Length: 98
Length: 70
Length: 57
RNA sequence: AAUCCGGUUAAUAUUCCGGAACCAGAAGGUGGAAUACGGCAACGUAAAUGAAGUUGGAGACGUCGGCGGGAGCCCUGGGAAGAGUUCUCUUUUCUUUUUAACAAACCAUUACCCUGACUAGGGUAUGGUGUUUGGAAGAGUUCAGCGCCUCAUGCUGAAUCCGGUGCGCUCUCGACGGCCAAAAUCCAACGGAAGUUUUCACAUCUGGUCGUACUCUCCAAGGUGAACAGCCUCUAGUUGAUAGAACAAUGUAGAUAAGGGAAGAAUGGGCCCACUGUCCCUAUCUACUAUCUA
Image 1 (cartoon, rainbow over the protein chains, first blue to last red):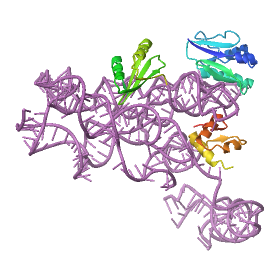
Image 2 (spheres, protein in one colour; image 1 turned 60 degrees about the horizontal axis):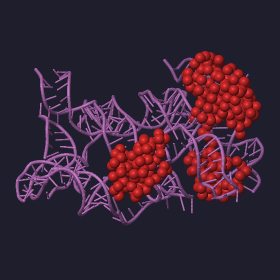
Image 3 (cartoon, helix red, strand yellow; image 1 turned 90 degrees about the vertical axis):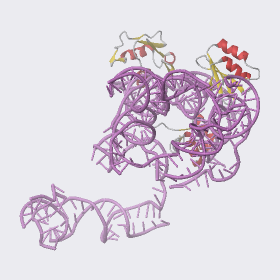
């Protein structure tokens, strides 16, 4: 139902995080009902192209949770100073540099 | 502040000298609110039909001060 | 030198307490000449002076 | 009798600014009706003569307790935004998320009237308490971006949402239970003197004098703790009262001390028992004073 789009064009251009790395991080950290990879059919994560990640969920999907999940990868990569997550639009999250 | 739902009354109100100026505010709901400030009350008429609002603006008295959206 | 009347003024437009302000320690020259509220409003939009967020309940 | 919002200063706001209303008083003008009405009823409408004289209501009323209604604070869930934590765990943690004055229609805890001979069926009024809208997003608040030698201090986007909870706290109103001011001012009635109507609506005007800056009985978060005891934090406000420097005696104070336990802390208990620097016999420590320097 609800569609969540995360823009990774800036990350791909700056090579901060690859689309596959984002997809692998998203797959390994998708705590659907507290279980990783438990998205099932209600929530489907399908990144169309290596510039963005799209998630279609039939249930509630918090953007802050996705941002919090995205913040862990940035903290792990230590790119928080040079890259910040921004709310481009309702349900749209993008990465912004300094 | 007295909202008026009668188009003819608003035209008659504009016809009388009691009216001072008329402001047409464009709302997000695409409804034209024709607000005319009189001596004792503020006459506001909200028209959803753009053509009706366009006709009302065209038919407004020349003496009235037509104001765009603030 | 004396920033007292300028910070106290800044807190008033800051709507919080006099101790709820903060600046860097190396811009004393350009804040000293800001006397009116319009000067401060220009400075807060610049961000040279700024509050700090509340820390916990 | 009658006003609120937002913004504005070096020092001002219900006063100033911008916007929006209300009151009182005043005349004439327009239009409306006018030469008052329906319901057994309580009562209702756009108006709908009233002299002298007579009457009433409000103003204008003691105190306490419990209950209901609402509001706000606080608490809490979801959404949005921002920040913080993280290999690890934490959809996490923290902060914020607005709608006045007044103007339009909607709605009883109570009482009255009709049917009934309390229960029960139909109406009646106050609608503080809400059901939308104007005011009113155009304002304010928070994010993201831009404008640029410049006092350019603007400009562009958005969001500014869905809720719930109360031996909580505050206040307000209302139905009960009891315990036992006056004056200013306003309205209405009876009344029937007189032979276009204004208490209907809209347009019109104006609203003097004085205090108003500033310093000090009212305003009063949460948690921990059983508690308004005690602490902590938040909000906010100080780091100010002459200091520095060293630590002997003296003096203040707080402690600990072997063995005895009134020979001079115990929990205190029932002369007895317990207890202890009261004493034998003082010793040690800390802090301050004392001491020096300015």
